[PDB]
Picture: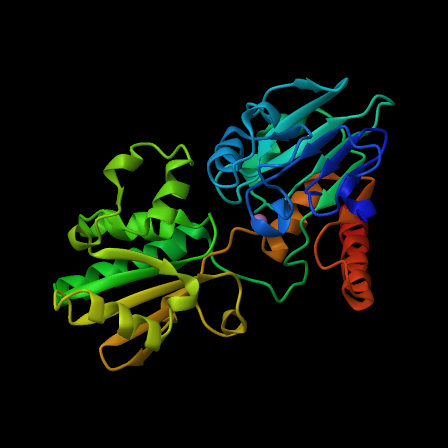
Length: 341
Ligand code: NI
């Protein structure tokens, strides 16, 4: 049974609610982005209207085989009427195709559902600037002040400088980057651009990337692993055993691996600066964990909410424990007292 925080009151709508069977009263199922915890339940046998971005609809048709007649892609930044209700999709600054949804209820209430997002001051000049929001359904993934991490730009600068130094010292070094979902593509694209290489990967991952509307993508990626010196592997293989095994397969072309694991936050963030990050090393293999986040830090979240000044907040992450729920509620009250709304 579908939980309340996935239902939009005063409508026939649900958000990211495909794992509950037929939801009573639901006339349109929205999907914020193509991550498995959110799409769980969708397949080629789904027969209700799915509303989403163009990029999410490309993934639904090619990866999950949802039939075309049930996919309803909407442009961004554009007022649309869905089953008699005005909606707008906004860029969420998460993975490719990820959106936030503004719903303009028939009674005058305005609701923002963030999906998954990484808040940014640029959102203060979207279509959100133009009217009041009553209710906020908020991605609270990192809603605690211990969760700090650098800008995406600082993390990419570290990765490119690290990779270019290593491969210039040793032209026989291979770079490997871990992946298990869409998102974080800048990591491996930026590294391959500084090295003058295409990124090599499995046929399954190439297919996924070909759905993402990235400009000039045919110039940047390939299934020909022999022609590439930046390889993508599943995240599970980014360990000394898995990398040893991969290096064997490369036919003595390479004699060293430099590997990256883009994580979200890890507790090494509470002590170390990005500049000071060091790898784990075993022989001719080195592994860097880099804190590349596609979710808001605590400070970015707080700034967004203090600007938006919603009347009510409904968390959508960390909702399963009383201690999490009480922590989040205390921060919301702090923010409201400090700002004066
Ligand atoms: Ni996500």
